[PDB]
Amino acid sequence: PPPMESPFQREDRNRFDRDRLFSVVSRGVPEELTGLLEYLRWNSKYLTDSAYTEGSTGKTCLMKAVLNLQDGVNACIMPLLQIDKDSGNPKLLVNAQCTDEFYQGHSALHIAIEKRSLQCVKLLVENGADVHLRACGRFFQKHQGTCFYFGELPLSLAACTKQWDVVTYLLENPHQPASLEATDSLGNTVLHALVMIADNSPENSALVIHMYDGLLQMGARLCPTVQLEEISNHQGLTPLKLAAKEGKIEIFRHILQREFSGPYQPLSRKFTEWCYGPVRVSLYDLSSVDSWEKNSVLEIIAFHCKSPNRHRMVVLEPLNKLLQEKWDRLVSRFFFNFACYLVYMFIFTVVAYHQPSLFGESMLLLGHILILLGGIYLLLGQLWYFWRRRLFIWISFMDSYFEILFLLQALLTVLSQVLRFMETEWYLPLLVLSLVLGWLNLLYYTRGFQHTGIYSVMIQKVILRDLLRFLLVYLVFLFGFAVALVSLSREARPYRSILDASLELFKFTIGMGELAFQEQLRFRGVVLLLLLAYVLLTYVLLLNMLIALMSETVNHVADNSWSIWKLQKAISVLEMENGYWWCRRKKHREGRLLKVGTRPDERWCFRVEEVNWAAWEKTL
Amino acid sequence: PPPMESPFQREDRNRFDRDRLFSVVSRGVPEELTGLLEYLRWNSKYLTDSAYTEGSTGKTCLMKAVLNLQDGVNACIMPLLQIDKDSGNPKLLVNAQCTDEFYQGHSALHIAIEKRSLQCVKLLVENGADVHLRACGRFFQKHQGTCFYFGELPLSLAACTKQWDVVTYLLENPHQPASLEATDSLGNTVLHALVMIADNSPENSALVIHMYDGLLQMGARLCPTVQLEEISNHQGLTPLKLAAKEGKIEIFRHILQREFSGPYQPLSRKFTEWCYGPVRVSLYDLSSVDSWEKNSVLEIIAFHCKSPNRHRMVVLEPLNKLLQEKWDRLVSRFFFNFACYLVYMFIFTVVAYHQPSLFGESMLLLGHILILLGGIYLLLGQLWYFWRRRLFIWISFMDSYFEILFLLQALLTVLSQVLRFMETEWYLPLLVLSLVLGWLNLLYYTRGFQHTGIYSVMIQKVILRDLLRFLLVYLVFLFGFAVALVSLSREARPYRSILDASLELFKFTIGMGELAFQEQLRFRGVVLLLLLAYVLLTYVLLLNMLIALMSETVNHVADNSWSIWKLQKAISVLEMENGYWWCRRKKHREGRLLKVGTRPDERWCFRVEEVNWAAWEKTL
Ligand SMILES: CCCCCCCCCC(=O)OC[C@H](COP(=O)([O-])OCCN)OC(=O)CCCCCCCCC
Ligand SMILES: CCCCCCCCCC(=O)OC[C@H](COP(=O)([O-])OCCN)OC(=O)CCCCCCCCC
């Protein structure tokens, strides 16, 4: 794509001509525009015609004038608009937009706002600039390349660039006021766009929070009957749900715990009830948060968010206490499920232990029937889970590999019981491997306790992703030395096959490597030197991997295992609330309906008791 | 060498004599010089004669006067010059220089500049001091001993000591102005000398950058038609190339990304094109940087620089994006080379696996021919590489040991195929060892991916240089206890040879050491005590080496593996751009020719798109 503006490269082409006009509006001298209007009238042409624009983009002379503002003012703008009006152009020059795929919908008002020229914005608005044109090119979309997403609207651009005067002028100018309800091509409003450009750094979060609160307070004046935070985009997300999905923890916490006093009190989501010393009791708005409603904040955080700080969101209030009462309500069902799986696995172990050769027989047949029925039940449950987690399936197993393991165990159980009916001998390794998987699957339920559940998070770490990368080097070492030892030992004056030599070389890592002078071999010295070289290289490699893993993991970073265990409990709770595949529970709504003021402002509120001695001592 | 000045040691000798004159010019009283001119006229002698100088160095009385400045002024200087003029000396005393090998070319103007006496500099220049005398002794060269390299010229001395007034006076005095184009004995100009004295500390870098920019701006006035940064020294290096070779990262980054506005705009190498929010688009000068030109900055960084921060240079713009587009253009050739090596190694493994005893036979002969041809091809390619990397060969394999390994593998392959024609049995261990090396050489191509290529940098570290130092102690332990166990076990009431006992003692480190009461030996108690002592000493040594290696490597230093992987990709790209030994590619020039102003200032410019949200938010 060509540059937006370039002092060194002339515009593409893919008497008053285009080059003279562009040079005049670049210099900014209005008196050199004389004769342009007469030339346009003589040739019956307009400034919006393709001959007077950049060929590749459709960038006009007015955008060239705004792109060359000197101290916020270009004197060629108003005479250019006067010439455009006097030429009888049915398409206004202020509303002309670029046509290329990279800068599609880009207009001069966007350039005037981005150049922070309030005078130019006023001059464009006074002459009929549409304040709802959407810059929807690839440069203005959100992706990993060179781009600037701010929404697509001029008001969203003015908000995302921290321009209070431009926002105030656009919202209530008498010519054409901008609407806070206006949406971009994705359905995003200005609050959605502020959530989009939000980062978790303190300065960006402060800017986004200030802009969000100010725009909400002005929406309380300009459109008081409009719920600005209840507007959903094309994904069905509100700004709170969008902040939950994108991992924008700071603005999510600010919206979730928002409190105002006096005026703008209906804009609050947190309402202080009473205080007594270090005890503070508050009411929290549960709208769009409680899992009783479809597509809630909790469901989005658990199953739709990809961000690494999902575990930091679930420990914020009121989410923490709400998930705590849900877990206290469902802990008996959790341990009943654990007891059922223990019974199933015990019968599995008894049946697999007493297999026959390739009253007791009837009991073994009954146990085989029970194993088949339990495998069918688990298979149907896992298939229902993966059907419900349809669209976000890649997000489903990135932290829930036990779902994959349970599905695989049930599939192996059903396959082994099918192969037993066909009387093939391969049912027994399948049954044994499903028994292995079933006993490994019992470690899912360690998350029911704090002591085991936190520890199961502390043990597993980034070792798994580096194990494969070390294994890539180690397998090359193993295969090369194995084929070498097989080739060299074929002549007599140990290593008969590739698998045997590979096993003997793998024995060195477990402390059982045989290292001897193979006197019956012809090349025994070279074989011994190859073994010693392999041992030294493998030990150097193992020391390298240990020290490298030691460098990334020991860094004194504070322990986040408690919040990850809380996130695991939240996922378990939200799955347990749906019931079973054969019996669906009716959802129970949390909180109480309370009137908190006048919009009667009746909301479902959750009461949270907080004790904080240091915070209370700081205000004395 | 004697001291430059010493209040305690008298000058060497290797009526108005030398001692009285030296004491007078040390005290600084001009009225005690009476009778010196008459004595010199009577004896027909001059102050520059060997009788009036230090014997070992040739240091004169004027240098003695300047070395004893009191508050920047010595009153004996002007009468001494008057006596020198009145004596009819054909050699001026101001231009007399020291003659010893340590202080060769040292003059009084250098001492006046180093003493920061602008009055003395003006006094010397007004009386005819040559401002282009070069201090070229061993003290003024650059080496690891006691030295001060500043260039060799008075202007370079004034610049390297941060003396703006002295530089300004030397550049435009009406008596004899110094030239910015003047070069030292190495061809270094003042900008080269500033690059030479540059350090990567912030204060030294700030001083060097300020001096460099000021001298370039004054060269824009004094010699506007002279390209000061295009001057090459005797090594053919410009100041940018010299900064790239010496690892001077700060001044290299400053020169590479230099930008000026308004006046001194032709001195810029970076030209901002357009900005829109956090997006900044700039043009970068590619002169002497692009690898299309011989001896470029990229080639110097990859193959000529010895400094440890080579990987920090390649991640700077515009080098990072340029190397990225080069890699995107050559990645298919990289993986085609990988596929060819995989095919060659697979045929190697198949041929080595199916060797006979010391249609299938014809296929094995064809495979032997293919192995021989591939070995010849790889040998010729590696020989061509080491021929092209002729002068800097020691810099070539300090980070590219795979070149050595590929050459050794090809040599072993050719030697094994030669020995097979001679029908000796030793071809088979050579073939097996070349197979080992060829399978190890496949790990070169892990750098083609980020995931494997970064990890291959993270695993290897300083363990290799400490492994040899630990091995020096461990081999002494092993040999001493081995000869002990062989000597002690010779008498009966296990260890028959040195190699056997060494292997049994090495078995303890791999977890297979045999530790038993050798009841058939006569000295079984002493043998058991020797084994226990060896085990304890070896385990203490291993624990020491593990903890010592743990101390140097775990230090929370930020990971530089990504930049080292980028440097490896840069080396691969620059080698792939030359083509093959049998087919040399034509170089493709990067960037576009654009006019950036008036010197028409036409440069080859590279467009770089940068997104930086925090930097843009800081200016709002
Ligand atoms: C169809 C109508 C008949 C229903 C019969 C009652 C079924 C109870 C189901 C139950 O408790 O589930 C236990 C377990 C499910 O694991 P999970 O979803 O918690 O975790 C899933 C992975 N996250 O599932 C199992 O362990 C398999 C059940 C088979 C053994 C039953 C033994 C009963 C002993 C009293
Ligand atoms: C003389 C005219 C005939 C030329 C025939 C084509 C040769 C292709 C060369 C090639 O792709 O090089 C692969 C490799 C070189 O390694 P490198 O320089 O990337 O890395 C070097 C170390 N850094 O070299 C090899 O692997 C050896 C080539 C022998 C096997 C060819 C198999 C072909 C299968 C299609």
Image: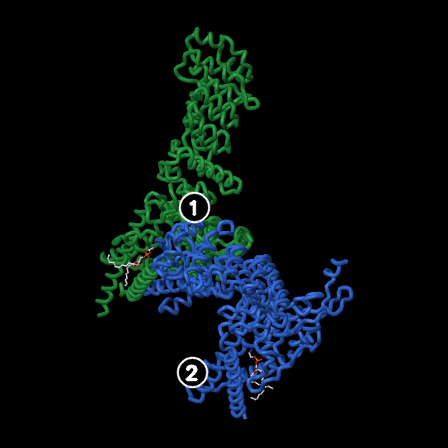
Chain colours: A blue, B green
Query: Compared to A413, does A11 lie above or below?
Result: above
- Residue B201 % position (x, y): 52, 42
Residue at image point 29% right, 50% down = B383
Identify the subunit bearing mark 2. Answer: A
- Image x and y of residue B351, in percent: 28, 64
Q: Which residue is the site of mark 1?
A: B256
Left/right placement of residue A141 relative to residue B594 reads right
Please give the name of the residue rendered at 54% of the width and 11% of the height, measured from the top-left corner: B32
* Numbered disc total: 2
| Amino acid at pointer 1 | Leu
Q: Which residue is mark 2?
A: A426
Marked residue chain, label 1: B
Task: Tell me if mark 2 has few (under 14), some (14-19) or many (20+) residues whose alpha carbon lies within 10 angstroms of its own.
Answer: few
C-alpha gap between disc 1 and disc 2: 68 Å
A328 versus A212 height, above or below = below
Q: Determine whether the residue tagged by mark 1 lies in a helix, strand or loop.
A: helix
Q: Nearer the viewer, residue A279 or A237?
A: A237
